[PDB]
Image: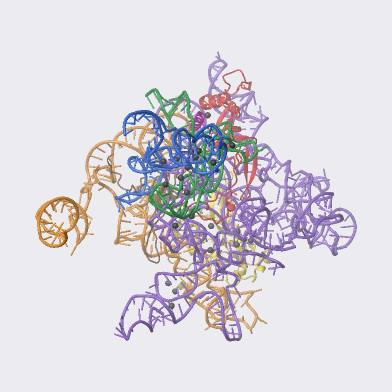
Chain colours: A brown, B yellow, C red, D blue, E green, F purple, G orange
Amino acid sequence: TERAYQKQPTIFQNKKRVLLGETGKEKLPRYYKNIGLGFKTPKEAIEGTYIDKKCPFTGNVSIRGRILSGVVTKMKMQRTIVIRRDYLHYIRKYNRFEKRHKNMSVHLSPCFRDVQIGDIVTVGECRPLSKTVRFNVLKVTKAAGTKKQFQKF
Amino acid sequence: ARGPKKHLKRVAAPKHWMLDKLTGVFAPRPSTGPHKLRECLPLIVFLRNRLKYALTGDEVKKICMQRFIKIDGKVRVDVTYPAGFMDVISIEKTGEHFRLVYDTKGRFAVHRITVEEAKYKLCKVRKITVGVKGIPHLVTHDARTIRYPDPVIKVNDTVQIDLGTGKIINFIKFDTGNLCMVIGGANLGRVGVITNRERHPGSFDVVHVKDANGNSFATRLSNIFVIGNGNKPWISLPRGKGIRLTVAEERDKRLAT
Amino acid sequence: GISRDNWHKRRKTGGKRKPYHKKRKYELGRPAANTKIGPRRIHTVRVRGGNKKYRALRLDVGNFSWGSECCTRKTRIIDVVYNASNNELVRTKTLVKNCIVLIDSTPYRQWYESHYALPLGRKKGAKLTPEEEEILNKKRSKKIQKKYDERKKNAKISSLLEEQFQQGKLLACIASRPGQCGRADGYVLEGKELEFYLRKIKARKGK
RNA sequence: CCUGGGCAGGGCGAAGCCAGAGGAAACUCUGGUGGAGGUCCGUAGCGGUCCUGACGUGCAAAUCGGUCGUCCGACCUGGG
RNA sequence: CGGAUCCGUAACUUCGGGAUAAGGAUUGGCUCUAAGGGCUGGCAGCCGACUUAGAACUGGUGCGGACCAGGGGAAUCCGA
RNA sequence: UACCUGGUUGAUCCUGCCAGUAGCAUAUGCUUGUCUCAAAGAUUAAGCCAUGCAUGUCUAAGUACGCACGGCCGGUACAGUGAAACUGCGAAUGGCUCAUUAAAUCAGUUAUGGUUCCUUUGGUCGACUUGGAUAACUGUGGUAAUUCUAGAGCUAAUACAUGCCGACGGGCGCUGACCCCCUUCGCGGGGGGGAUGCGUGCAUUUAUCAGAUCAAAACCAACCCGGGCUUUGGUGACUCUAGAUAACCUCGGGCCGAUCGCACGCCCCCCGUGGCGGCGACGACCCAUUCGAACGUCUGCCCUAUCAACUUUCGAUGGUAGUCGCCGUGCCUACCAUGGUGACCACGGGUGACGGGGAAUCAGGGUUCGAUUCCGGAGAGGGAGCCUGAGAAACGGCUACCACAUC
RNA sequence: UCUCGCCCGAAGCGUUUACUUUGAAAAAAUUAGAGUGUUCAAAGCAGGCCCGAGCCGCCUGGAUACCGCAGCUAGGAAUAAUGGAAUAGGACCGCGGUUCUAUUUUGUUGGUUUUCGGAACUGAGGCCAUGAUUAAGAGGGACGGCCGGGGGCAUUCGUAUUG
Ligand SMILES: [Mg+2]
Ligand SMILES: [Mg+2]
Ligand SMILES: [Mg+2]
Ligand SMILES: [Mg+2]
Ligand SMILES: [Mg+2]
Ligand SMILES: [Mg+2]
Ligand SMILES: [Mg+2]
Ligand SMILES: [Mg+2]
Ligand SMILES: [Mg+2]
Ligand SMILES: [Mg+2]
Ligand SMILES: [Mg+2]
Ligand SMILES: [Mg+2]
Ligand SMILES: [Mg+2]
Ligand SMILES: [Mg+2]
Ligand SMILES: [Mg+2]
Ligand SMILES: [Mg+2]
Ligand SMILES: [Mg+2]
Ligand SMILES: [Mg+2]
Ligand SMILES: [Mg+2]
Ligand SMILES: [Mg+2]
Ligand SMILES: [Mg+2]
Ligand SMILES: [Mg+2]
Ligand SMILES: [Mg+2]
Ligand SMILES: [Mg+2]
């Protein structure tokens, strides 16, 4: 359901299908956006339930510019996660590298479920969503270990 | 700074204007027009510096308002009017019909053409759109916005334009096998047949071209001007086909003299 | 003197940024004008690039579109209920982009009579309103065409809109910015959104 | 010594306990709960610092009015 | 000065304190808004509690409006 | 120029430092004939300034009854030069300096599909001339003066305003009297025409509908022919552009020439009292280009731990909606969640720190400067606010405070 | 793959960084460096041949090299790490069934159904040489004959000194 004041992006609701009286299905008026770029739209945005203004597959957030990748660190921020990008910096004097990283926040779309900490995520440049969020989660690639295992309870 | 810029330094001037270091401090800043400041050539540079018609710039400023020099059919009153690639320059008294084609080194090579070809002009389509009441518009890099062009014009095409009426004719498409001329980058003025395009989703695509005697280079789509149709250029280009051979071959040509 | 600038802010961590600008011109801030429900009164605002902005200090008229049947007529703005962003502006009666306006349901009744004859909202009196209800007599086959419009399409405007037409108020959502374009343009709440906002207004009147 | 009676309300927040976070470990940090004490402001009660006030052949052979110290106690107090 | 609420609190130290340290703001009236529960039916409905926070308006800056009620700081000697 | 030398000892070897050696760029001492270039109040004091200048501008083409000069010159306004004013443009440029500023500014690279844009370049541009107002000008004045101004009279326009004709009404939507054909005794059903009335074009602000990759039949009811028919483009991606549907289009009111000059000819008619007007200047609603601006992505900066936790009631991080803004935004507001950064050095301080392209230094590697002529930023004693303007928080603009400071 | 015209274009295309070789990449000035007798030179971007003045003249230059680090594209697969299949929920090919829809021919429209194109779910079987590199003169652990004035607790002995 919804836990806000209004959630209705673009699609007009009432077709007034009532010619003799029937309930029918209501999941048919759903907005479906193709992001292009050779990247597959997940089926959670097809048969989902969520309504997100800042979703790359539902909202008006266009994906442009650069495409980067990172590893997810935290989930405690609402509908957006913080990733880490480890890289090396070449130094001219000593003639070898050093580890550097810059933690960035990125808008995690709620269609990307099973987004457990440690997975390699693809991010894309968009418009500035908030003060520290500029990228947008695009595709979750790695399962970050064996999902086949199960423990007690 | 506040607002737009208003002057231009000789040191900050682009290299292809052949300006000096001892002559003056300020460079002639071109006025706003169809071409940007890095890919244009002013009338005072074309007259005072290149062809050597007047020694001082005040004489050029006098004659351009005494209505001798005209660009593309109509007379320009500005001494610093921009005139970029593929512009017809004619002055009204003798056979002087100059084409602003690019030299192999990147300069503006002069090219005097007969009047039967000086009447016409090629131009690259910049984009295509639709406008009021469902009519098609075409925007040219020469800042020509023309209505009802044709339905079979791709965005990166080259269309012949008439100067007397402003009518389009003879469109040529971006296809493998057409003779093109590079108008920007490190390989500007390079004339070669389009060999292989490579598309990329990052809004910029690369093109490998080949020309005669076994040479190949690469460029981007923002620096490609189609000039011919299968080793048949619609505009006669001066000093051979416009090929950079080798610096050593240039020295050998200078020794052969 | 209002600055919407972002150079007086903290960093990713929270380090205080040092000030060196002087709150420049391209980062303007103008004070808010709470659009009341009085008569029509709109001032002008100069905008960079020589543009003109229409600041509506108070408004009476509005342009609200019916949802399903695709009709749009004039509207007198009556009352402001359930801003759902700041409840102070409900008491203040300020017209914002996403607010709810009580349409006076009179200018839809003439269109509903003219296209969807045998109308409603007559409180089951069946003796009043000599409107020209039964004067034109519906001579030709356009009577049959109106019969297709009235019984085959069946004109279902089910009981929520029925009760709102009987009460004479129509709950509508604004879709335009009243302080920017000077227009209180919007649409009529229909169906699931209608019952959702009706449930919110009922719960707000309850608790 | 024996046997009985009494001490309005608030402040500080010990031990113990719970939850969250960090650490490899030692353990640490934060938010609560808890109500400890010859503890603090203060009433009744017990004494009497100052005005060296009033009286000063007075109400009184030691009292009165403010200002007072302490008031869970090494506390006050009846009877045997 | 004095009550209460919101900030912020030093030298020194036995680390417990110093501390209600020092130093500021608000306090009236009248309308509202939000939060803090119980009881029935396989989420819906009925009934009361005085608390907190926020907003507008207004009275001659007037709000602990009477009463209730810590002036404070730096030091020395002695007695913990 | 891939380089050393003297000094601890009675004497020798080694670590070690000191002192000589040579550029560099600041000052200073002595001396100085020619000639080509040539930095030059940066270091302390982004301290104070007397005096003189650095921003003005007219074409055949905005407005000329100036009292100024004067064409031959008669009269049916205006020959021409034309001082001064009204109007438009620019004074947001250039020059100067580096005081703040340490992921801030800058440098390399990417996009605005999240915005504006002077001017230029093209498209679009579908009543034989109305109204007040006013300067310069004439006389009259005030004060100690200023780029100070009042009141009396006058006139102008591309300053301000108001506002008409063309142009047949094409075509479409909704009502619409009436009419034709087939069937039924009529009732009734189907198909096809048809004036009045409201609308109508581009933009503004809404809401809705249709909008491309894929070909073979079988049952039931209506109708056309001789078994047989129908359509905008682009991106890698759209809530892009373009159509249709009902209404506002906002008095501080988007546009749809009440403008000027040159060359002067042609045609019909009863007269021109009517047309045919070729070219040029103004921005004028919008669309793109150009000069850019603006916030955005990644990466890159000196020292300090005697700066190890920082930020969050005065947003710290995110979400939901709204306000402002040119738009995307905790830029701001109400509610909700408790987040975000850090030993891979954040946070807190100092810089005698504007960042670079660069400069000096001769194996390579490095070290130290870069205020300085180019680019970008910042400021005009400190610091706040704002009109005009497309562009300013402007200072050779204004307003108020502080420190100076003239009559 | 033959979906769009016995081979190719084209699209599925990259498991992804680190590293190399191209290529675009930027703005000049400055630095190395082409040409040039500025009287040589520091510079400058110039100038040079014919003509007795009479050719109402011709020809050429104003390049290149670096532009680290960061970003983009196309080749390379040695070097260093990363997951593939261990409770099989793996890999290919071929089968049974359920629900749904875009568009074409039945002359067109309206109602019904199938093949077809695909996403979603589900049951069985065949198929793989069906799937785990052996255990470092690396390491942890286990066994057992020892060994050590190693540690802790309790006990026992010895003179001597003092009284
Ligand atoms: Mg400047
Ligand atoms: Mg109530
Ligand atoms: Mg006590
Ligand atoms: Mg005390
Ligand atoms: Mg006391
Ligand atoms: Mg006493
Ligand atoms: Mg006494
Ligand atoms: Mg007495
Ligand atoms: Mg007491
Ligand atoms: Mg007391
Ligand atoms: Mg006490
Ligand atoms: Mg002290
Ligand atoms: Mg004290
Ligand atoms: Mg002492
Ligand atoms: Mg004592
Ligand atoms: Mg030395
Ligand atoms: Mg707040
Ligand atoms: Mg400084
Ligand atoms: Mg060197
Ligand atoms: Mg070196
Ligand atoms: Mg900037
Ligand atoms: Mg400034
Ligand atoms: Mg000064
Ligand atoms: Mg200035």
From the viewer's side, name the closer residue of C90 and C65: C90
Q: Quadrant of ligand 7?
A: top right
Up the image or down, D72 lies above or below F121; here it is above
From the viewer's side, name the closer residue of C72 and C90: C90
Up the image or down, G20 lies above or below D15; here it is below
> Quadrant of the rendered structure where residue F82 is?
bottom right
Residue C43 visible to an observer of this rendering: yes
Which stretch appears magenta? C187-207
Coordinates of residue F145 in the picture (x, y in percent): 78, 60
Residue under the image location 50 percent in, 57 percent down: B222
Left or right of residue F20, residue B108 in this image: right
From the viewer's side, name the closer residue of C5 and C161: C5
Up the image or down, G7 lies above or below E39; here it is below
Coordinates of residue C50 in the picture (x, y in percent): 63, 50
> In terms of secondary structure, what is the magenta stretch mainly?
helix
Left or right of residue F249, residue G88 in this image: left
Residue B182 visible to an observer of this rendering: no
